[PDB]
Length: 50
Length: 184
Length: 69
Image (cartoon, rainbow over all chains, first blue to last red; front, side):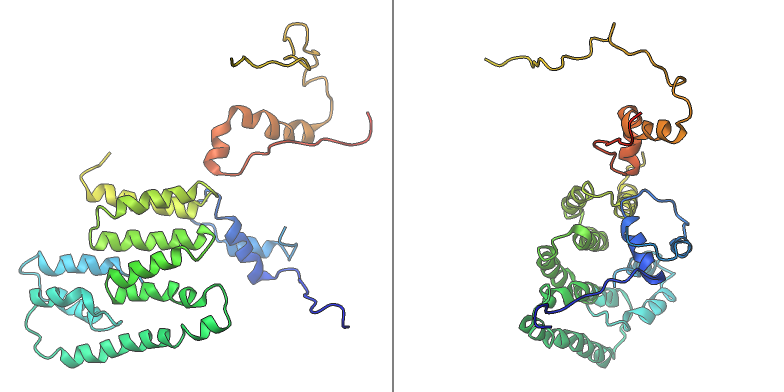
């Protein structure tokens, strides 16, 4: 216990966290208006951020 | 914020230039002028308005609330530097200077935006600051300041794709090239 | 003085009696990999502008592997 100062867990993302990973990576894509990214994020049941 | 800010500039046009149509326009703008802490942009509009003889307490209740948001910035700037984040003085009022951009004039905006331009190492806050400078430069028709930061905008989009910052940007020249008589 | 470029190894695949004359119809049953090597090699070679226009960063190099034969 004196060896490691703090351990940090990384969970798989949830529905609120799959949205903004989509939001950041859809920045560099040329999109079309009317997408509803919320419906896209719910199709993936928490795969990862990769 | 600067997001409902363009309808104000349309209603200033709706106030003055239709000469007979200057009654409901001076009411519904004053419906929004003496609320949401606006102080600076309507002194000469009040000169183009009627007397409105008692506006003194109408100003004093608002310049106090201007100072209230300004003094809690004055209470933020020492608690952010004691245990620092990413310069959280600036990082607080890099979102609260756009308030001061709406509330005060450009001078509180321009000395704080060029402050916080050098803070963020990524353009994802920088290029959103540049959209603020474009939008006030349309209100004050800063036709020589928009020529500077548009190139400084466009120089940021090439790294990354930034299509929500490119297709957003194309509307701004699209409104500027129709502001000037350049239809093609 | 400056020079035109030069190498010995290899030269440039002399283009007359150098193609190994195998066509796409010879390779039977490789539908994924025949399609997907197109998108990484010669489709960005010719249609370079769409990758620039959508902004999807075409791949620099490709590593193909597997069991022998």
